[PDB]
Image (cartoon, rainbow, N blue to C red):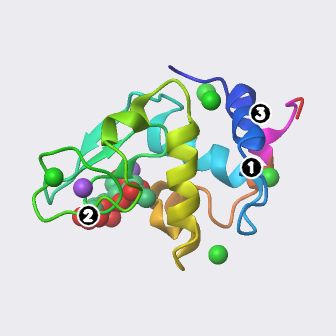
């Protein structure tokens, strides 16, 4: 599924991401925009052979099992394919674990490079939330 911006904002809000670990909702929407262009089916392969999955491009090196990232962890205890669902629950729940892990949203490269330090509230501007 390719979410609309506000649709995703609302979904993320419903799933408890607004101000989760101090990260306002726009951070999460911004991260999703730049990680996946709001596409739950996005996958990208990393240089180490892991793959990033879903709307928040959560990687299989650490967070999910895709059966083809040897030596990796599955800290969200999910098949990576669950992160491709049109239902963002698995991604959100995993993202909550990630962002809680001490590094905040810096885990999301695109967030660090494209959202951090910007007016992320713009990403939820105009949305009914
Ligand atoms: C939370 C999450 O999974 N974020 C992804 C990053 O992990 C991806 O970065 C890449 O992650 C792999 C596995 O840890 C690293 O080997 C790789 O070096 C790293 N790539 C960079 C450029 O840092 C990122 C890839 O675009 O996608 C999500 O942000
Ligand atoms: Cl868009
Ligand atoms: Cl915000
Ligand atoms: Cl694996
Ligand atoms: Cl959802
Ligand atoms: Cl933080
Ligand atoms: Na990415
Ligand atoms: Na894994």
The residue at 89%/29% (across/down) is 128
How many angstroms separate mark 1 from mark 2 (CA)? Answer: 25 Å
Crowding around mark 3 (Cα neighbors within 10 Å: few <14, some 14 to 19, many 20+) is many
- The image shows residue 11, relative to residue 113, as above or below, that is above
Q: Which residues are magenta?
A: 122-127
- Residue 10 numbered tag: 3
In the image, taking residue 27 as reference, residue 83 lies left or right, namely left
Estimate the x, y position of residue 126 in percent, counting from the top left.
Answer: 88, 31
In the image, taking residue 109 as reference, residue 50 lies left or right, namely left
* 82 drawn magenta: no
Residue with the mark numbered 2? 73
**For this rendering, which residue is in front, 75 or 99?**
75
Disc 3 is placed on an element classified as helix
Residue with the mark numbered 1? 16
Crowding around mark 1 (Cα neighbors within 10 Å: few <14, some 14 to 19, many 20+) is some
The residue at 15%/45% (across/down) is 67
Q: Is mark 1 in CB contact (under 8 Å) with mark 3?
A: no
Q: Quadrant of the C terminus?
A: top right
- The image shows residue 68, relative to residue 41, as above or below, that is below
In the image, taking residue 55 as reference, residue 60 lies left or right, namely left
In the image, taking residue 122 as reference, residue 115 lies left or right, namely left
**For this rendering, which residue is in front, 44 or 62?**
62
Which tag, 1 or 3, sits closer to the chain's start? 3
Is the shortest distance between ligand 5 and the CB of mark 3 under 8 Å? no
Estimate the x, y position of residue 73 in percent, counting from the top left.
Answer: 26, 63
Q: Residue furthest top?
A: 1
Residue 70 lies in what quarter of the image?
Answer: bottom left
Is the shortest distance between ligand 8 and the CB of mark 2 under 8 Å? yes
Estimate the x, y position of residue 21 in percent, counting from the top left.
Answer: 71, 68
């Amino acid at each position: 599924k390719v979410f609309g911006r506000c649709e995703l904002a609302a979904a993320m809000k419903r799933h408890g991401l607004d101000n989760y670990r101090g990260y306002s909702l726009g951070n999460w929407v911004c991260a999703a925009k730049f990680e996946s262009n709001f596409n739950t089916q996005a996958t990208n392969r990393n240089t180490d052979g892991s793959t990033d999955y879903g709307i928040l491009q959560i990687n299989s090196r650490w967070w999910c099992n895709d059966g083809r990232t040897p030596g990796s962890r599955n800290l969200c205890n999910i098949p990576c394919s669950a992160l491709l669902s049109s239902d963002i629950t698995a991604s959100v729940n995993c993202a909550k674990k990630i962002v809680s892990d001490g590094n905040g949203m810096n885990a999301w490269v695109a967030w660090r490079n494209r959202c951090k330090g910007t007016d992320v509230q713009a990403w939820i501007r105009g949305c009914r939330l």
